[PDB]
Image (tube, coloured by chain):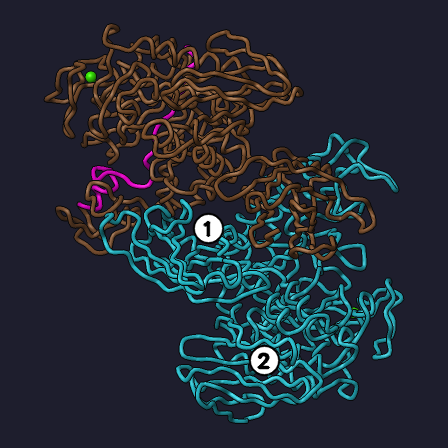
Chain colours: A brown, B cyan
């Protein structure tokens, strides 16, 4: 085999504990290069004469270029040393250890996970493990209070086409009045973009972190929303913009007024006084030259303490978690301490980050619980919407992403289809509902947390921002209730099948020609197979099904009963039809 | 080329800052697959059409199977996105980015280092970058006070052969009395194995963390050692055993007495009660069933606070650093907070760990400054002492180890030849002094911090523990002063040749037949080439020396001047001779 292509490291995403006495280990090798991967291990202080325990590393998956092997090590001493025994297609074997590769075990050396501390076991909120989150863009969801509308608010109608500076009056009172709707839909949590006091239309340039923006509501109303959502089994997640503040932030205005005499000049990154200009600025800001968004020096103990107080304040209001904005630009220590604070106040508070690149540095268990799965969105867009990639590529992309982080993170990644910053998925699908539905079916049965962008469930459409921010369609006759019932049904299924929320994922079938992809979700003895016919043609396929997993399945969407003959399952799917096969266990 | 063997990650040892505006990036590829590696980068918010910056990545080295390329990205904005352009032997142009490999730059995507915070720039003590440490085993270095000698103390003679339970009377006063000797040698720091109060001979089972063991001295004496050492330019490093305490430790004694009602039960890992008995252990200990060494629950904030107080106490006594014992079995948060405490009290205090496996998880810059370089010892033992490996293999092992961690850690790793737990290095060489000297010449000119085991500088020999712990030889007649002068000379050169303490390392020549290895240490315009003729034969070697780095060199050990002709340097080395060639810059 090709030894230079084989990889493992005793940490990060390749070695991490799932409990105090169990260590998961993963290894990658060029696809097809390794046929068998076994792990020989023992306590780090074990005598050189004792027998080593054995652990077979099953092939957890494979992407465009690699095969991924995964094993679980039982380490009652919480300390383990181990070496891999690798076998190729032609029977050639080799030991792989920290020292390197060798036909002799001793010369391969041994990898070591020094000690498994209970406090370092990646732990996430149980409720987030089976949640369906709904993204609320406040200004455009529901206008429950006309008296707080910004001046110049435009009419709330389906034919409305939003302009960058448009206003429709969406607010918290509206969300409250519409909680019955969200409850009927079945969402378990609401995620809000920024809602704190700000002079702009977007609110990403915070003026007051301790107040709800007047156009959206106030503290008493927010408290009411939290309470009303909670009794309906709906949690509240707020967006925290801690990387930078608005130029109206008390600390910044003070600096603008006193210059180098400000007690807060060091809460920011200023090059030289006086501090200001139009399109030009002597201080660091979000992105490039954004005057209204001065970057905060979170490394400053005072800044950090202040933001922590902000976090305490909202959590005292009863919120259930945070979505962090531009989190990759605030330091790690802040995030490690943020987590300690947050979890001490509420062990079930969720911490989600938004990083548009490999987020492994924030997903080891000491910082965020998860991040936005932009990779999922990209794979779903190109597979279901644009048709730029086929089923096998879709499979590879999905798998590569899956292997990026420890299972505790991957399990809670927010899998979005779109956002207030993208065109709506329906529009990406060129208005084709059959394509849109297949994507939703996949979204609701795949590994991760489904995130619904407001209005998508009733068939809203729209080009990218600001056209994706049209006012929510509330007139029942103008909503797509067929789609709505589809989401509701899929959501009910996700909650009834433990596999869909807490199961692992394995590719079941991938055909680039028929463009059919199938995968299986598994937990204990339960298996739920999902078959996706992503083609505008009726197609027949033969899936492999060794009798050990069962020989009878029920399509949870139609009630049809299918049977495997001699370890094979023949299926005929209608155009863009998706089946959710439950093995009855 | 083998794409599955190419590696990089935007963190850890492959992407890290050396300053607030400079990011070092490294890439690994199968040896020979890549002949040219360039990096195209820009600010993360740069417009798609803006011109990308260029940085050529020079080949930093090669080990058994891979080439390692390194580049320095200039990032004024402290935010950077980048993609590699790899050129193969046949001129194939391959782009490599977060997305993957592609012939098109856009499809390869881009790696991203979101933000460079000054607090995350790995920083180590300046004095430690050019230090020469001396390991003192207190019981055997010098007996300055017989009144504290334990009963049964044996004769202090060169012909003494220690037994497991022998006693010779070494103490702190002794060290003070011998400071003139240590100052002459030129050592800048003293590292002590455990010296706190303990009932055993070894003292790894701590009875009182706040007291010097009576047989070694008292607090007033320790203070005198700190002050006297300091005025001699010698710092003091203590061994901290925070993973476990002794069964005589007050908290544990209390647990053994009050059991379930003990205020300190959660300070340890207790299975059941009664707390203990002879030959039976119901509590976790260091290693396996070591009743005298109960593991401390450093995750317990009370234990943490107590150990931190211990650290505060000794630092108040003016010590300059800590060598951690069994550090990999104490949690990371404890080490991160420990570093924060230590550096806040004394930014120049050093923190060294002892981990017998990849220690990258502790060498990112937020925990330890360095660790013991056991890989260095293994390589020099096989290359210089036993002859198990040749020059090219030696080159490989060195290079591989060098690429394990960020440069700030590699630069300060403790390069030891032996220890109180191993046979003496001279003995490893079978008493061959010529071999011993070449290894020391190497130790004193290589990347890292030279650690001298007490007595090696005057020719002491010995089998492994306890024979390596013989009474220091203080009779000038019995000391190998020739060797002593050799050590003094090398330490002197190390101090005046900046490239030897702060320069990078680059293999210059490696030949498995002649068993000759040469490397170059570089800092700015200064180059110091070390040529090691590790063979019992006078040999001639032709080294490549492109005129850009100089045409004339001075061998700092002989005063011999050598000249290059047409980009080549002809050298003739005697058996086991080493040359230290300074380019006069
Ligand atoms: Ca309103
Ligand atoms: Ca004594």
In the rendered image of this protein, does residue B465 appear above or below residue B574? Answer: above
| Mark 2 chain | B
Give the labeled residue for mark 2.
Answer: B491
The residue that appears at 43% across and 33% down in the rendered structure is A394
- Taking the image as shown, residue A345 lies to the left or right of residue B241, namely left
Q: Chain of mark 1?
A: B
**What is the x, y in percent for residue A534?**
40, 24
Mark 2, secondary structure of its residue: helix
* Residue at 57% from the left image edge and 46% from the top image edge: A29
Residue B413 sits above or below residue A298 on the image: below
Q: Which residue is mark 1?
A: B9
Q: Give the residues in magenta.
A: A232-256
Corner quadrant of residue B135? bottom right
Res B17 seen here: yes
Answer with the quadrant where ligand 2 appears in the image.
bottom right
In the structure shown, which secondary structural element does the residue marked by tag 1 occupy? loop
Q: Nearer the viewer, residue A431 or B155?
A: A431
- Crowding at dot 2, Cα within 10 Å, few <14 / some 14-19 / many 20+, comes out as many
């Amino acid at each position: 085999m090709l030894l230079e292509a084989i990889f493992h490291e005793a940490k990060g995403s390749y070695a991490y504990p799932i409990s105090e006495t169990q260590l998961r280990v993963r290894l990658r090798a060029k696809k097809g290069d390794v046929v068998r991967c076994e792990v020989l291990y023992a306590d780090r202080y074990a005598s050189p004469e004792e027998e080593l325990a054995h652990a077979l590393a099953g092939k957890a998956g494979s992407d465009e270029r690699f095969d991924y092997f995964e094993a679980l090590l039982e380490c009652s001493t919480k300390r383990v040393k181990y070496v891999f025994l690798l076998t190729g297609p032609q029977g050639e074997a080799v030991y792989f250890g920290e020292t390197g590769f060798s036909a002799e075990r001793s010369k391969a050396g041994v990898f070591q996970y020094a000690y498994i501390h209970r406090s370092e076991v990646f732990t996430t909120p149980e409720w987030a493990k089976e949640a369906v989150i709904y993204q609320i863009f406040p200004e455009r969801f529901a206008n429950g209070d006309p008296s707080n509308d910004p001046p110049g608010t435009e009419q709330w109608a389906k034919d409305a086409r939003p302009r960058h500076d448009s206003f429709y009056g969406g607010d918290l009172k509206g969300v409250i009045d519409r909680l019955p709707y969200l409850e009927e839909l079945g969402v378990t949590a609401l995620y809000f973009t920024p809602i704190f006091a700000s002079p702009s239309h977007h609110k990403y340039d915070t003026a007051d972190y301790l107040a709800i923006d007047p156009q959206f509501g106030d503290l008493p109303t927010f408290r009411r929303l939290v309470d009303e959502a909670h009794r309906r089994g709906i949690k509240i997640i707020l967006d925290a913009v801690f990387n930078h503040a608005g130029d109206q932030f008390f600390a910044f205005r003070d600096v603008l007024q006193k210059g180098e005499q400000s007690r807060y000049k060091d809460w920011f990154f200023i090059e030289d006084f006086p501090v200001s200009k139009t399109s030009r600025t002597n201080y660091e800001t979000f992105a490039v030259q954004v005057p209204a968004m001065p970057k905060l020096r979170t490394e400053n103990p005072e800044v950090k303490e202040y933001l922590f107080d902000v976090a305490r304040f909202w959590m005292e209001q009863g919120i259930d978690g945070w979505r962090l904005d531009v989190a990759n630009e605030v330091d790690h220590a802040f995030w490690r301490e943020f987590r300690r604070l947050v979890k001490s106040l509420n062990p079930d508070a969720l911490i989600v980050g938004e990083i548009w690149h490999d987020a492994s540095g924030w997903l080891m268990g000491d910082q965020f619980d998860s991040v936005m799965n932009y990779l999922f969105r990209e794979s779903v867009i190109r597979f279901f919407a644009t048709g730029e990639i086929h089923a096998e590529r879709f499979d590879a992309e999905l798998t590569r992403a899956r292997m990026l982080y420890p299972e505790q993170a991957a399990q809670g990644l927010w899998n979005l289809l779109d956002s207030h910053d993208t065109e709506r998925f329906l529009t990406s699908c060129g208005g084709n509902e059959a394509k849109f539905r297949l994507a939703v079916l996949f979204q609701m049965t795949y590994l991760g947390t489904p995130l619904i962008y407001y209005g998508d469930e009733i068939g809203m459409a729209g080009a990218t921002d600001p056209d994706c921010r049209r006012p929510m369609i509330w007139e029942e006759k103008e909503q797509n209730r067929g789609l709505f019932e589809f989401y509701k049904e899929l959501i009910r299924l996700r909650h009834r099948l433990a596999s869909l929320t807490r199961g692992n994922v394995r590719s079941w079938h991938a055909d680039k020609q028929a463009n059919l992809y199938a995968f299986v979700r598994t937990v204990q003895d339960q298996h739920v197979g999902v078959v996706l016919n992503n083609r505008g043609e009726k197609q027949t396929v033969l899936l492999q099904v060794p009798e050990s997993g069962g020989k009878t399945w029920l399509d949870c969407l139609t009630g049809e009963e299918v049977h495997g003959k001699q370890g094979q399952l023949k299926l005929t799917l209608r155009p863009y039809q998706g089946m959710i096969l439950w093995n009855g266990r």
